[PDB]
């Protein structure tokens, strides 16, 4: 029967690919590997010359990949995301100079721009009547897969006391295996913009001069540009700030995997506890992004103020609570933006909100972090994001009056 083969051989493989594509045990230990003794990079080379290329090339590969995710029907970009991940972990094993690691982040931002590849691959593959179940099984296999990689990465370092190079060699045994699984993925019969079934890009602009008159799209798409640009400027640099607090050899005590597993677990509890409040807390929505942004302002300042190496555990939990605070709003942000919009347009306004959050992320990184513009250290940059989230909290809270 073609019903059992469409679930046991397709959906049980679709959740298995989304599990195994997220298995990267050395994902949370990239910057401890670079700052470690094996690669010997200083904290000024990774903060001012390597990680700014992660925010530059992500501007340069966002709109090419998003236009080529739909032209190729999502399967070569799901192959490109897996194959560029192999190219990252080859440069983390065969790269010495700082010019090699600037190519490591350029290949890493390809895998950052292709996060919407697999999320929109399930929309084009499965039937529209049975999409809410398969995407429910797909977001419970990626989120399980991105939680297991932070636990398997942590357990194979703390419990199984091996070096970081043994860990990232294990991470090639789960990334070449994610290229093999991405070869055997079914190309969907339809796309979203280019390979349709048959106005396009004329009906949408008619449905955008009037949909932008809505106040929630005038607010949450203005939160996605600015609050979700300073959020990625923390997550890129918080692994350097943890290494500035407690620079440690004897590598079984780094605990970056447990602060990425707990921030996924709090990024799912506070996301599941956000589906209950996306309807009720829609009246004073600008007050909700005024308290959480101020909660994100007090946690970015807590990261920039801890100094003793024995107080790093109140610095991991300042990031687990930070990553869970942003993950409380994106279920509400992806609902209040995609409420009245069509699926051929809400996934377009998420290609503008992400692109405008990447111009802002490129503006701040060239101004506050890159060695050509200012070149600040990772602690004097995190005090420039505590002001940035607090300025964003005397705008939404000040805007709550008007």
Image: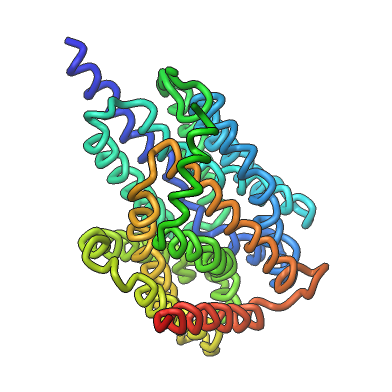
How is the model colour-coded? rainbow
User: Which residue is depicted at the point 25% across and 39% down?
Assistant: 137
User: Which residue is depicted at the point 56% across and 45% down?
Assistant: 113
User: Which residue is depicted at the point 57% across and 59% down?
Assistant: 357
Q: Residue 282 is drawn in which quadrant?
A: bottom left
Locate the C terminus by quadrant.
Answer: bottom left
* Residue 359 to residue 283: above or below: above
* Residue lying farthest to the right in this orientation: 372
Give residue 206's position: percent from left, percent from top: 49, 40
**Which is nearer the eye, 315 or 219?**
219
**Which is nearer the eye, 371 or 401?**
401
Locate the N terminus by quadrant.
Answer: top left
Give residue 227's position: percent from left, percent from top: 51, 68
Q: Residue 372 is drawn in which quadrant?
A: bottom right
Q: Is residue 102 visible?
A: yes
**Which is nearer the eye, 272 or 342?**
342
* Residue 395 to residue 240: above or below: below
Q: Is residue 313 visible?
A: no
Q: Residue 189 is drawn in which quadrant?
A: top left
Give residue 238's position: percent from left, percent from top: 54, 71
Left or right position of 371 against 363: right
Give residue 45's position: percent from left, percent from top: 74, 67
């Amino acid at each position: 029967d073609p019903e059992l083969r469409s679930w046991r051989h397709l959906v049980c493989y679709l959740c298995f690919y989304g599990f195994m594509a997220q298995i990267r045990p050395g994902e949370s230990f990239i910057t401890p590997y670079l700052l470690g003794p094996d690669k010997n990079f200083t904290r000024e080379q990774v903060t001012n010359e390597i990680t700014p290329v992660l925010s530059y090339s992500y501007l340069a590969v966002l709109v090419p990949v998003f236009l080529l995710t739909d032209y190729l029907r999502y399967t070569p970009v799901l192959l490109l995301q897996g194959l560029s991940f192999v190219s990252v972990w080859l440069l983390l094993l065969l790269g010495h100079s700082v010019a090699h690691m600037q190519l490591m982040e350029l290949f890493y931002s390809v895998t950052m721009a292709a996060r919407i590849a697999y999320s929109s691959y399930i929309f084009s593959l499965v039937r529209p009547a049975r999409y809410q179940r398969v995407a429910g099984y797909s977001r419970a296999a990626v989120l399980l897969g991105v939680f297991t990689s932070s636990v398997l990465g942590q357990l194979l370092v703390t419990v199984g006391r091996v070096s970081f190079s043994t860990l990232n060699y294990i991470s090639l045994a789960f990334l070449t295996f994610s290229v093999v699984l991405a070869l055997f993925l079914k190309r969907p019969k339809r796309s979203l913009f280019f390979n349709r079934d048959d106005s396009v890009l004329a009906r949408m602009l008619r449905e955008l001069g009037d949909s932008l008159r809505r106040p929630q799209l005038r607010l949450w798409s203005l939160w996605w540009v600015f609050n979700s640009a300073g959020y990625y400027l923390v997550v890129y640099y918080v692994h350097i700030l943890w290494n500035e607090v407690d620079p440690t050899t004897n590598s079984a005590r780094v605990y970056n995997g447990a602060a990425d597993a707990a921030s996924t677990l709090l990024g799912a509890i506070t996301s599941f506890a956000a589906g209950f409040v996306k309807i009720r807390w829609a009246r004073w929505s600008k007050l909700l992004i005024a308290g959480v942004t101020a909660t994100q302002a007090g946690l970015v300042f807590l990261l920039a103020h801890t100094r003793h190496p024995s107080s790093i555990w109140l610095c991991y939990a300042a990031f687990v609570l930070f990553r869970g605070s942003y993950q409380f709003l994106v279920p509400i942000a992806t609902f209040q933006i995609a409420s009245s919009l069509s699926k051929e347009l809400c996934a377009l306004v998420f290609g503008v909100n992400t692109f405008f959050a990447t111009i802002v992320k490129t503006i701040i990184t060239f101004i506050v972090s890159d060695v050509r513009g200012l070149g600040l250290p990772v602690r004097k940059q995190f005090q420039l994001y505590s002001v940035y989230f607090l300025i964003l909290s005397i705008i939404y809270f000040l805007g709550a009056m008007l």
